[PDB]
Length: 188
Image 1 (tube, rainbow, N blue to C red):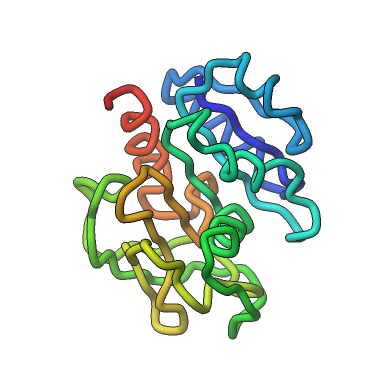
Image 2: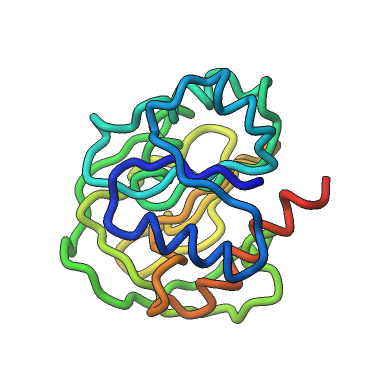
């Protein structure tokens, strides 16, 4: 079971449908779902979805505060990436290109979610906002010309962020990145 916390973005269903296509048990829940209830689902992984506003992240930060009750892989997508960054002591701010487009990224550490993938990928993303200061204890996994932090992970915990939307088909290997993340939740 991969739980997708709905932060209100336009592409949240695509995350769910991608996982379904992959044969992964998954459910979208309101981001305001109480933690106990999230715990009663026995999640093997959690996704913090995109959305319009850091002011509407519901209990995403609460999940991180209580990570010891979960101890499963977490993937933040765009706003989810940014909220993880803020929570862990990094900084988010405006980028230089607010419109969505395909952007080429360079994978600098294939780690887990980029395992087996090419070194450069075009991904569907905006930089209306982005991570400006990496959190302590995190490492960068991918970059682009205008944004050094296109993907990141905690150095010690399976907590991941991507700035772009792997759930959008335009993203090269987007389905594979989601698959790689799901495979992490099935092994430990």
